Amino acid sequence: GKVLWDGRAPRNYTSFHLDASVDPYLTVVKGPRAASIYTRLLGREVTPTPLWNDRLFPEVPYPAVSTEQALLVLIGNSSVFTPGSSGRPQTGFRRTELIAQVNGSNIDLIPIIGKGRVAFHFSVLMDEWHKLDMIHEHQLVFVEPSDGSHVFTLQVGSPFTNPTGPLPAPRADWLKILNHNLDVLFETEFTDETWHNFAVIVDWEKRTLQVWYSQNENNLVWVTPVLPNETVKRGTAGRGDFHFGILKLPLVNVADPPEVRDDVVHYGIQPPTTHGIMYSGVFIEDLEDGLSVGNKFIQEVA
């Protein structure tokens, strides 16, 4: 497909780009500290997903060159988002997200990534240095319309419930792709030291989702059929911004009055700990000629 937006960090990207909030990422969804304190560019420390490598000839000595650097996205105790200059701090959440933009604007991108059939690509790698706590729910990747809903979500960790139930939940450490109604479409163990490659095809006319998945250098394969996603709102209210990072939900604090425990934006137990996840291969393409499945192959889809 043609690339509509490329969030694969160039090898020459820097903290300074991040602290200017320039293309390709809007960095506003974070705590008060600079964007670069929460999101680190990993240079040569971490090899990104091999799917988008370039290959060398001859194939000895080095087979390939990385075309991107991985990103490490961190949350910590300062990761409280204040919406605007005047919003109530989101004290229930710990969040750091990057949002796709083009020419300085997320708004202008909405029509481009919101029409026809669009493939949202992203690959995750477990951070062994600041482990995610799977007792809590983490919303990692999603497209968020105006109303705060998610057309689809990549989630990991035990889903938030009020009241609190057995924790960890079964398969808490499985990466999960959810539809807009929070139905589990596909789930797979978040194995360590492994690039978990995803593509979610959104057909904006028919309101469908299809999940594609692989590990490491393996080409993406389809792991769901084309599935109805019919709770998405009609028209422009169904479209929204592409986020990736970590949105960590709290647990219920029974000390809180029953009338506020459901309000996860402002209430709940959040320990003051640091947690990370690494991203690579994050980009958006249409389905011209087909889906990019990795390793310089395209696959026809319909």
Image (cartoon, helix red, strand yellow):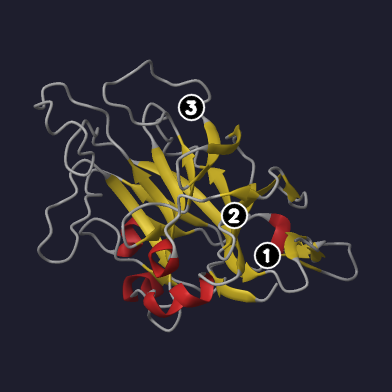
Rendered location of residue 282, percent (x, y): 56, 61
Front-most of residues 186 and 101? 186
> In the image as oriented, which residue stretches furthest toward the top?
166
Question: Regarding mark 1 in the picture, which secondary structure is present there?
Answer: loop
- Per the image, the residue denoted by label 3 is 172
Estimate how packed mark 1 is, as few (under 14), some (14 to 19) or many (20 or more) residues with alpha carbons within 10 Å.
Answer: some
Question: Regarding mark 3 in the picture, which secondary structure is present there?
Answer: loop
Q: Earlier in the sequence, mark 3 or mark 2?
A: 3
Rendered location of residue 166, percent (x, y): 38, 15
Q: Which one is in front in this view, the residue at disc 2 or the one at disc 1? A: 2
Estimate how packed mark 2 is, as few (under 14), some (14 to 19) or many (20 or more) residues with alpha carbons within 10 Å.
Answer: many
Q: What's the distance in space between the residues labelled 1 and 3, CA to CA?
A: 32 Å
* Rendered position, 104 above or below 269: below
Whether the residues at callouts 1 and 3 have beta carbons within 8 Å, the answer is no
Q: Earlier in the sequence, mark 2 or mark 1?
A: 1
- Per the image, the residue denoted by label 2 is 208
Q: Earlier in the sequence, mark 1 or mark 3?
A: 1
Q: Amino acid at mark 1?
A: Ser
* Rendered position, 35 above or below 112: above
Direction from residue 198 to residue 221 in the image, left or right: right
Estimate how packed mark 3 is, as few (under 14), some (14 to 19) or many (20 or more) residues with alpha carbons within 10 Å.
Answer: many
